[PDB]
Image (tube, rainbow over all chains, first blue to last red):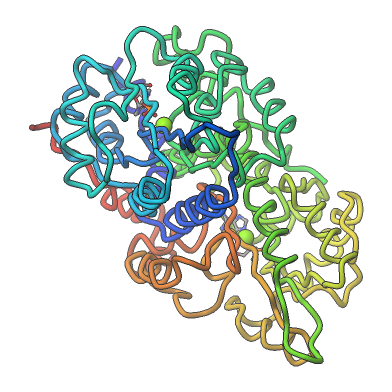
Amino acid sequence: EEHANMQLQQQAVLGLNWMQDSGEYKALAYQAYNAAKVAFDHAKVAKGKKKAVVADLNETMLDNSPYAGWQVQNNKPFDGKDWTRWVDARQSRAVPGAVEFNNYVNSHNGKVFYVTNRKDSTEKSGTIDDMKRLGFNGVEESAFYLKKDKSAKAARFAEIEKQGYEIVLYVGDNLDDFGNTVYGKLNADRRAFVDQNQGKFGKTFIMLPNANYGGWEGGLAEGYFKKDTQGQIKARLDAVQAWDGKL
Amino acid sequence: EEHANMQLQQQAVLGLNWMQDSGEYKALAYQAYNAAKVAFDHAKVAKGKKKAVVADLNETMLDNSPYAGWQVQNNKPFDGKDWTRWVDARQSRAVPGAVEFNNYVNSHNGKVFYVTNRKDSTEKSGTIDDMKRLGFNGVEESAFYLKKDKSAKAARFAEIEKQGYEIVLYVGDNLDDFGNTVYGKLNADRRAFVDQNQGKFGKTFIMLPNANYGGWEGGLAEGYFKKDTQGQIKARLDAVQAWDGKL
Ligand SMILES: Nc1ncnc2c1ncn2[C@@H]1O[C@H](CO)[C@@H](OP(=O)(O)O)[C@H]1O
Ligand SMILES: Nc1ncnc2c1ncn2[C@@H]1O[C@H](CO)[C@@H](OP(=O)(O)O)[C@H]1O
Ligand SMILES: [Mg+2]
Ligand SMILES: [Mg+2]
């Protein structure tokens, strides 16, 4: 149904306005990257280890909001085939503060590795071209751990550690950018993970804001991503906590 | 039109799900307050001055998401008269990390002052009752600078400084919580203010995320808050930046 597709995407409009237009979103990005620099500078690693920073790309270092905008304007729910075309369009922007932090790490005895679920086989060329144009240093192919078979990221973090690096901090907009412990889990377990790690945020886990999509969307209901459009609309509306209007 | 009221509030649903349900939102709250503690501990003030922290309430220290949820469920655009009833309902929650940071400041040679546009005359009693119940220390009436005549906050910051305090940091979800320089201005000027203060975020300006409302909403278009419901919907949709779908 086209009506359902329209309602689903209309539900993203206000958060998209916030991410695209507000100074507040920019301030949060700068806040995150300012905190990240402090954590990096403070970090000490084991003897023999090299300092690594792990960074997610989409909505962490790369700004894909125009794809979301296209979804809104065309009543288009997410489709990986449309996403691939977006990547190939080479119109990605940079999240504020990301290039500076990236380049600072790489010039101060660290290395940023990009652990990202952009696809290695079909989305790598556009990703690298955009990042070069955007001013990121260190974007040789060896810095990238793009998605091959698995969306969960922990195995790639381990690959990095096997190369002689100690990861001093992680940057992301999705809790699954910090490990696998709540990958595919509902929001109750994900909030619990955050509580169990309260002191790490702004130190070793650096958060960027993303009100448009993510593991929290799937976390709204068991089997959310398997539901049809109407089912997803209902899951979102059912998750809403509302005042009863009484005193 | 009821159809317009419904569309306007439907546009807030996804960002509301994110704020209410996601671990990511909690992580951002903890990140902000972890950073705030570091800044407070580092702060030095002029001889003779007492250390003050200025904090906004709504969506900074107090969580009002159930009011937004009620708006969604009842197709109700914002109305200060409904808001007053919400305050009186005494169902406010605390933003994660806020009580701990508040109480830490107040027990470590500082004072948090609440500079908030909850209304002094009609909304003070519910505000204080909720904050007491939520566990905030230092919520005597003298800590509060609630709205009387003016929504712009700088004059109240000055009142605090005249009492012998030096403000060491500001906490908020709205750029207008940091001063008056972009109060009532459009988002271009507000983003410019953020850029001009890039290094302060996460240090002396502490940001909390709010994808549901704020000065950025009014900032979407000249005279936004004066427009009717259809006009506001059009302003939001017109602000959207969209990929053209081409390569
Ligand atoms: N609406 C959306 N739904 C799922 N993924 C999206 C998305 N918008 C952007 N993405 C990105 O596509 C990859 C696979 O999930 C992820 O890459 P990252 O690991 O973040 O670099 C998404 O964020
Ligand atoms: N949807 C909304 N629109 C305007 N204000 C809202 C709002 N939801 C909550 N508020 C709050 O009402 C006061 C006046 O603007 C502000 O208080 P604070 O200065 O943030 O404590 C709003 O955030
Ligand atoms: Mg991401
Ligand atoms: Mg506020």
